[PDB]
Amino acid sequence: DLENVKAIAIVYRELSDGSQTVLLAKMKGKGWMFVRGHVRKDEEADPGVAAIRETQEETGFTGMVKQSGAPFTQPGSVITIHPHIVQVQEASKSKDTEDTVKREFLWVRPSEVRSKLQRAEMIQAWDQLHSFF
């Protein structure tokens, strides 16, 4: 892992009427979040690969990157974050995803997303990319 490079994936599904629904997550027990994880050294040339991998590991869904936003920087608890919009399309077949981490999930309409975000990092990712919806 690159310790100071992260990928965010704003995960959505395309609906039959041309609207979208966005997946939010929370570690039950600071609001809601998108998919987030470290970019591996072998993904540094295309952090969108990390976004798809993290989406599979967290949700059991796979799909494609629809938009890669500009990287942004955040202070450490500097982190460079690469935000993406990921359309999930099919179930993941990845062996790694046979055991996932327990997580709370919520599908919402795009109009519901911003009020569910409390952390600067997710607000920045949404601010850069929400016009896709």
Image (spheres, rainbow, N blue to C red):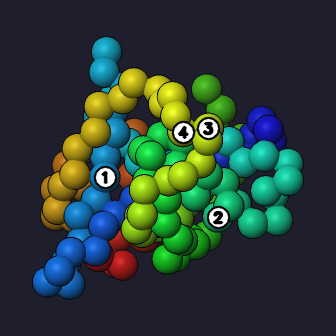
Vertical placement of residue 38 versus 43, above or below: above
Whole-percent x, y for residue 32 in the image: 31, 39
Secondary structure of residue under mark 2 = helix
Distance from disc 2 to disc 1, alpha carbons, whole Å, reads 18 Å
- In the rendered structure, which amino acid carries the disc numbered 1? Leu
Judging depth in this view, the residue of 75 and 6 nearest the camera is 6
Q: Name the residue tied to disc 3.
A: 96
Q: Residue at x 79, y 38 (%)?
A: 1
Whether pointer 2 and pointer 1 mark residues with C-beta atoms closer than 8 Å, the reply is: no
Q: Name the residue tied to disc 4.
A: 97
Instruction: Tell me the quarter of the picture where residue 17 sits.
Output: bottom left
Q: Name the residue tied to disc 1.
A: 23
Distance from disc 3 to disc 2, alpha carbons, whole Å, reads 18 Å
**For residue 77, side relative to residue 42 (left or right):** left
**For residue 79, side relative to residue 128 (left or right):** right
Distance from disc 3 to disc 1, alpha carbons, whole Å, reads 21 Å
Distance from disc 4 to disc 3, alpha carbons, whole Å, reads 4 Å
Query: How many neighbours does mark 2 have within 10 angstroms: few (below 14), some (14-19), or many (20 or more)?
Result: many
Q: Nearer the viewer, mark 3 or mark 1?
A: 3
- Image quadrant for the C terminus? bottom left
- In the rendered structure, which amino acid carries the disc numbered 2? Gly
Query: How many neighbours does mark 3 have within 10 angstroms: few (below 14), some (14-19), or many (20 or more)?
Result: few
